[PDB]
Image (cartoon, rainbow, N blue to C red; front, side, top):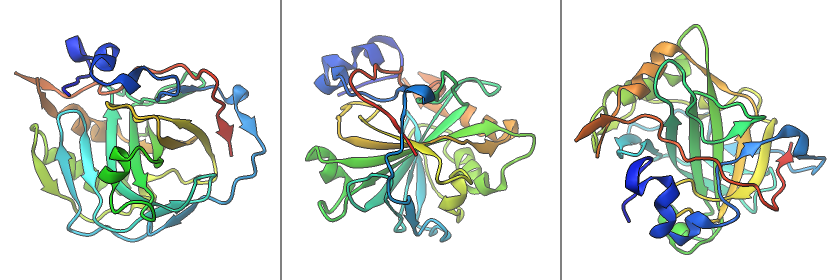
Length: 257
C-alpha cells in the first residue's frame, strides 16, 4: 500500500491500509531514562563481523522514503536480551530539514537528534531471509544509532556521505566504498536501551526487538548537507523530515543496560 511522511497518506492515515499501524506496541517512542528499568543483567552485547571492512558488493539506494544500504557481508549481533543471534540485512536513515534540525525517530528524555540510523536484523536460524521473517511475523531485531553535530567531519562516515552524493535522485543506486560498520556505532557499546516495539513504517508490524544506543556518533554540518540534498518523487521535492511521529508506550517498560 502507498504511504508517505506527510499529506493524505501521511502517518496519521497509515492505519487505513495497514491495521497494525494502530497497535499499542508501536515505535518509535520517547525514552524517559527515569522510567526505565535497571539491573536486568543482560548478556554482553556481542558484534560479529563489525570490524571487517565492507565489500565492494554493498550498495545504497534512494528509496524515496529513505536511503537504504543493502549489506552484502555477514554481520551478527547477540546478547543484550535478544532472542538469538541476529544477522544484519540493511541500514536505513531518518533525518531532519536543515542546519541540524530534529530528524530522529526515537528520543531520550525528550531530546531528538539530527539523524537516526537504523540497522535491521533477522534470525537466520529461523528464516532464509529478512523478507520471509517479516512476512512470517517473526521477531526481528533493530538497532537505532543517533548522530550529533561535531565541528569536524567524521571520517568513518566518508563512504556513507560519498554514497549519498551518488543517490540524489529517487530510485538511484550506487556501490559504496569500503566502510567499517563498527565505526558507525557509538564508541560506548555497553550503553543502550531495550524495548519491544514495531517497524516504524507500514506495515508497522509489532515484531521488533529494539536496541537504542544512548550515546550519539559525531557528524559535521557539512556531512549533514548530503542528507538534506536528497530528492524524493511525490513532482520532485527534497527528501526531508522522513520520520514517524512518536507513539504511546502504553504497558511497555524500557530497560537500561
